[PDB]
Amino acid sequence: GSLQNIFRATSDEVRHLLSCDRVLVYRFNPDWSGEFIHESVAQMWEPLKDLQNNFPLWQDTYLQENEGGRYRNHESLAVGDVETAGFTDCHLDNLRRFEIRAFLTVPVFVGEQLWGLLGAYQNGAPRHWQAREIHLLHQIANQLGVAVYQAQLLARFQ
Amino acid sequence: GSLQNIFRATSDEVRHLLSCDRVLVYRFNPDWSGEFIHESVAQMWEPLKDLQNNFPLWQDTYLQENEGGRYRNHESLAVGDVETAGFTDCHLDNLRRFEIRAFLTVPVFVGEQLWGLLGAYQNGAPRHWQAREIHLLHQIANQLGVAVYQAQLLARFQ
Ligand SMILES: *[C@H](C)[C@H]1/C(=C/c2[nH]c(/C=C3N=C(/C=C4\NC(=O)C(CC)=C4C)C(C)=C\3CCC(=O)O)c(CCC(=O)O)c2C)NC(=O)[C@@H]1C
Ligand SMILES: *[C@H](C)[C@H]1/C(=C/c2[nH]c(/C=C3N=C(/C=C4\NC(=O)C(CC)=C4C)C(C)=C\3CCC(=O)O)c(CCC(=O)O)c2C)NC(=O)[C@@H]1C
Image (cartoon, rainbow over the protein chains, first blue to last red):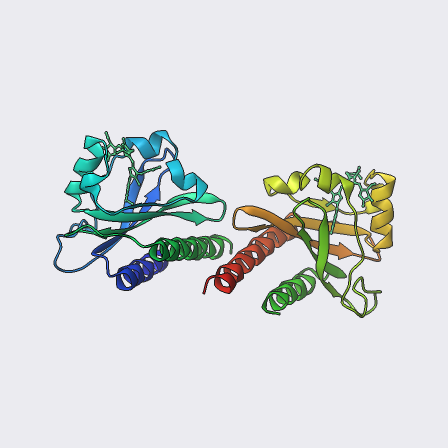
């Protein structure tokens, strides 16, 4: 619950600061598949989280094959319009499925590890992401990873 | 000053908890030489820090050649009596110079990086370091590294 509070605080903060439509926290599994573990979403949009607090699966073969991809280097990806990005069909279909028109996705490092990703999404319109927003999100994610690691340090020692 | 407060808090905490004679924070330079940047020492012992707040040089060729040595793996070294440890003369002479009879030295990780070391020292007598003290110091150091990284995140972004 203490972790969910941290995810909720960060995700709502992002959504508030960037005035995006949806924020997602995605956590990598050991095999580099991953799970959504938090969503902040404006009420006008169908939420990804169902009433059991389950999420849908995004089975991203590319992240998994590349063991986190660019995010291993602490890089982000900002895409203003998914429909003009030249993506592979299976990837675009998931973007469409999750009502992602434009996204800014940054890595979450927990100590030395690429623990997950933090995504900010625009749902109804493309969005030209500014350099400052990319830099800000990256900082928010670093802060989130520190919060996560701090919580782990306290939760499991004494 | 905000960093010195963190070093002072941690170092005094260690010295208090382990009832050792001296605690040192050592920070690695880019070339894996290093500098002492804080000491907590019981009043009975000559301090390493002079009145200018300068420290003496410990020019450890082995740490430097091995780019941090065992500490890169997050390992510690606990030595109960330096005089029976089989050390190389140049290393033993520095131990003697700094009035180190027994030491417990752990790595300080700042995010993904081996930033430095945290050392607890007994000055006047050997000391059998217990597994629990090794495990505790390791945790204190992880916490210190998190504090350091958090301070860096806040100091240099906005
Ligand atoms: C095809 C069978 C499947 C597929 C392929 C695929 N993915 C990518 C690139 C990425 N996939 C993602 C994943 C996410 N973005 C997010 O916002 C979230 C939630 C936080 C996830 C899980 C990301 C970020 C990228 C860019 C990665 C990078 O290192 O640059 C590719 C490469 C680009 C392309 O489309 O050609 C491919 C082929 N993804 C699926 O979902 C399919 C089922
Ligand atoms: C010889 C010219 C010089 C030298 C050699 C040397 N050092 C080591 C091993 C270590 N040196 C240290 C350093 C410290 N211990 C501390 O508590 C602090 C302050 C925080 C420092 C800087 C450490 C921890 C080790 C163990 C490292 C590891 O990876 O295990 C060796 C190897 C062991 C040996 O003595 O044979 C050698 C040869 N050190 C000097 O100071 C000389 C000038």
